[PDB]
Amino acid sequence: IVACDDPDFLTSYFAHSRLHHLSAWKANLKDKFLNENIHKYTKITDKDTYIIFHIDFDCFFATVAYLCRSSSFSACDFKRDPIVVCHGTKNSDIASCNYVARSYGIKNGMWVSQAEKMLPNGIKLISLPYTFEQFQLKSEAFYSTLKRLNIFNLILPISIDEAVCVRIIPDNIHNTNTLNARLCEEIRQEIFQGTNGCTVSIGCSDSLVLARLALKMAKPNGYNITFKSNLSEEFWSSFKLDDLPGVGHSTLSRLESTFDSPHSLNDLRKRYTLDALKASVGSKLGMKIHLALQGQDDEESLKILYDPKEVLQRKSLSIDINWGIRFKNITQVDLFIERGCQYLLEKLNEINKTTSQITLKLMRRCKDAPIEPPKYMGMGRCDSFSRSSRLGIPTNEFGIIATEMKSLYRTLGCPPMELRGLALQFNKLVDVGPDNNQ
DNA sequence: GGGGTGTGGTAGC
DNA sequence: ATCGCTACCACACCCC
Ligand SMILES: [Mg+2]
Image 1 (cartoon, rainbow, N blue to C red):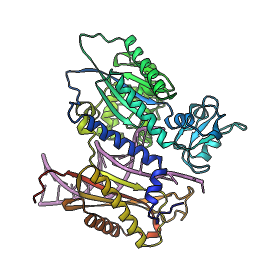
Image 2: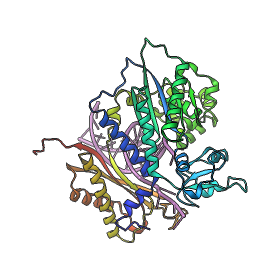
Image 3: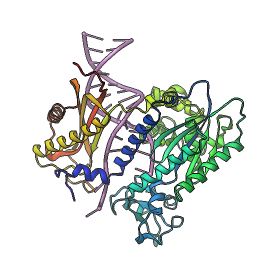
Image 4: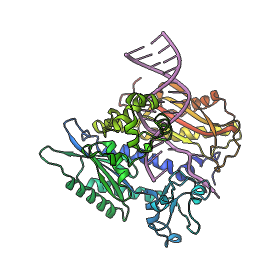
């Protein structure tokens, strides 16, 4: 056990935090793409008619945690057993669940206690540990297979287990759904072989958003082909409102109230006006949804296809620790902040940049929230506070940055014993050139 | 027209 | 027990 005031707390928390792994893997995938392609030209022109194949593993962690499970779990059955991947027993997040578990209405993000109660008696939840290193290797095999197929002109990494693959269709070639079925089946078979038993599903379409929706419809272990020319009431009636990219619980709730609680995108599609959309959720998001309900991508989402190198270039660097934060005094907070900056400055040296603006964010116990929340070591119910600060000369100097961060903490006025979470950000990054003379 | 800030939402498992 | 990260866009409100 390593507590927030121990020197090794940052290292142990990140080794254990799957959310860190997700983010660290994404970042490495993004930088890897930029490296492979520094000399190649990674763009899709407006000259190109293209097909989008949106690929991702079916219940990634659960699948892989099963396939590499320890001897204690040799007899458990991925097709009959409700399986979750989690650290703990009570208020531990279900990082991933197989589709047997979902049949009982369980979803990721749910706590293990909550999911235990949606099972009939006698049916027992299986809880698998995380296998991070195997998660990596299976992902490597995933992207290695996608490249070896030589059927894609651009392979965009979305996630450790998710990629958007772009096929350019010359106008001499007449695309057909038969040929698209055969590609999906090739891809699915080849990743099944290359990953020793992991299955992917594929959405296939002539827009990013319809490929995202097709993919939801393809799950589990299948594929779906739906171009703009194939749209139908049957299609839209199949999706919830928060199946739309950009629509999370907050946008959902706003949409639900403005539009008489639509229960499908088909419901949404018939009742909506562009301006009532914009009014309900916002101008840019409203437009994105409007375009989306026609099967069309917006200008912001098309950028990744036109200039992936710019969209995938890292613009900020940060850490976030909102679990395990329990400090008795201001000295321990300052030393933790210093470990934080030291960590971020290593990462910042790796990418050979300086930073010219930094931010500190914190979570403070709500005045009426219990000192110890339901989730062990959780941040609990919190107000957030943020404050940023421009540096004069861009820099990678620990002395300047750690001093300013501690100053920022101090302007925020949060007693060490009320602290429940900390973020440390480098907001603007500046390249280091061969010229360094003033 | 151009800056700026802090805040809030969303995405992957 | 339990590991509630992190990048990025958008917005609302401020300034000369
Ligand atoms: Mg959604």
